[PDB]
Image (cartoon, coloured by chain):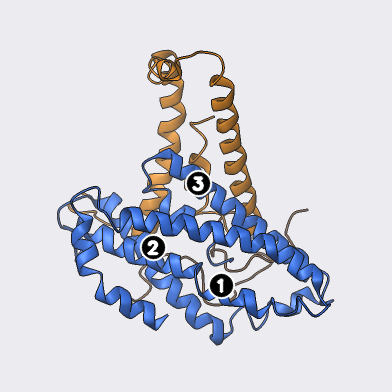
Chain colours: A brown, B orange, C blue
Amino acid sequence: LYFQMSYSTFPKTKNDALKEPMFFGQPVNVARYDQQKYE
Amino acid sequence: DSIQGRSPNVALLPLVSIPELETWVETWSFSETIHSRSYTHIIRNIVNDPSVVFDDIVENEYITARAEDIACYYDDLIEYTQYYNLLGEGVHNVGGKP
Amino acid sequence: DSIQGRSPNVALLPLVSIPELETWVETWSFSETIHSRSYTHIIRNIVNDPSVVFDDIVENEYITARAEDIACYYDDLIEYTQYYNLLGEGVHNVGGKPVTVSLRGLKKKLYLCLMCVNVLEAIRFYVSFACSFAFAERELMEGNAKIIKDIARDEALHLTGTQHMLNLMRSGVDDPEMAEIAAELQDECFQLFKKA
């Protein structure tokens, strides 16, 4: 393939899964859709 | 409403981290799409020439001024995000000029 | 279904020209979102630990293998489109090393990915239907079948749409350029198909 040139579609594992910034940081990898950061 | 139908998704999805906001922007785009469909429906029973209304309002300066004003420094964000993702941190030189 | 929730819009919207297809991909994304909501609903009343199921299946190699296989040469198309838009035609040098260029290169790297898209909603998700569907005639978990019938209808509409799109674009080339792509990317297409 390649050597991870830049941002990817979604990561292979978890990064934080609960406490990421609003619209900056790692991409989305799984939609839990039950526990969110803002009600 | 057509100037913001596809813009928010293509401009915000590559940056949003939490998926619970990606779902919301998807629903926003879908709702905007339904709005466009309803507009096409309400115009399909008023004037017998639906191909004659998209002549002036398509490129009327009265609306084109604000259209360009809202599009220029909105696509600027998209192109700058593309630059940031394709170059990363630190200064560079994209084929010649820095 | 989460691996293709946001992918098609962010991967195809910057390239689609006719808006009548942009509306369709928007509705596709919305339908996928509704699917995710329905899955979260059906899992919210089975196991009292919804935070315990996203531990293995989140990064299980059994599924992670195919996940990476479907994601690698699908984000390749997105990054190549970004390159093409940020550099244009003609060779360049992106900060040192030279940058390649290709007009037809922005077709195969897309078209083959679309093929994956097809099998992403034609076979791999289509067997899981029957796997989770045999518990229908025997009276048990009828709510699962009731909620999955609509998802099956939705998946079938997705299949019809994507197959029609492929047969219209990849076959019967309107523009006189993708015929070379159909000729070249033919045997490797069957190879990757049998591999999947």
Would you name the residue on which mark 3 appears? C24
Residues behind callouts 3 and 1 on a single chain: yes
Residue drawn at x 45%, y 58% as measured from the top left: C162
Under mark 2, the amino acid is Leu
Would you name the residue on which mark 1 appears? C126
Q: To which chain does the residue with label 3 belong? A: C
Task: Give left or right: position of C55 versus C83.
Answer: right
Asked whether residue A27 appears in the rendered view, the answer is yes
User: Which disc is residue C183 wearing?
Assistant: none
Give the mark nearest the N terminus, 2 or 3: 3
How many numbered dots are placed on residues in this image?
A: 3
Dividing the picture into quadrants, the one containing residue C193 is bottom left
Task: Give left or right: position of C142 versus B59.
Answer: right
- Near mark 1 (Cα within 10 A), the count class, few <14, some 14-19 or many ≥20, is some
Q: To which chain does the residue with label 2 belong? A: C
Q: Which label sits in the foreground, 2 or 1?
A: 1
Distance from disc 2 to disc 3, alpha carbons, whole Å, reads 16 Å
Quadrant into which the C terminus of chain C falls = bottom left
Give the mark nearest the N terminus, 3 or 1: 3
Question: In the image shown, does C133 or C1 lie closer to the viewer?
Answer: C133
Q: Position of residue C163 (x, y in %)?
A: 42, 59
Dividing the picture into quadrants, the one containing residue C103 is bottom left
Residue drawn at x 60%, y 47% as measured from the top left: B25
Residue drawn at x 15%, y 53% as measured from the top left: C90
Up-down: is B27 above or below C133? above
Quadrant into which the N terminus of chain C falls = bottom right
Label 1 SS: helix
Task: Give left or right: position of B44 versus C12.
Answer: right
Q: To which chain does the residue with label 1 belong? A: C
Distance from disc 2 to disc 1, alpha carbons, whole Å, reads 17 Å
- Near mark 3 (Cα within 10 A), the count class, few <14, some 14-19 or many ≥20, is some
